[PDB]
Image: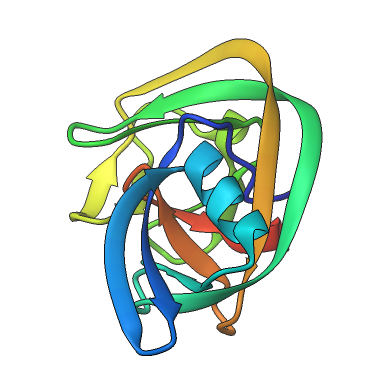
Length: 145
């Protein structure tokens, strides 16, 4: 289990450097480059508000699935953990149509689940006890414990 995402996933981040603060929507590809630049402290938007990213993880190639609600769609690793309405965690590939999940717009039911092609994936640590963040607008578990 992880929070692993491919390069094209979109997250909302906040960059800080020496009093400068910037809020940006970025792909996970761009986030990796910003992380490896070493120039910033990076926070990510979450249902707990912005939280600092700690460690980064290159996860290699994983099996992938597409999960969509009415408002949001993510392509994520098969074992990318997504938060249910009851706040428990489930692997993306084990979601079924109708399941209520947490999103940036509140609870929404899953409308579509589809296996897709393998992809290079990435994960990271979120420095908050809930260890969660918005990935493509869907509440995801960072480092996927």
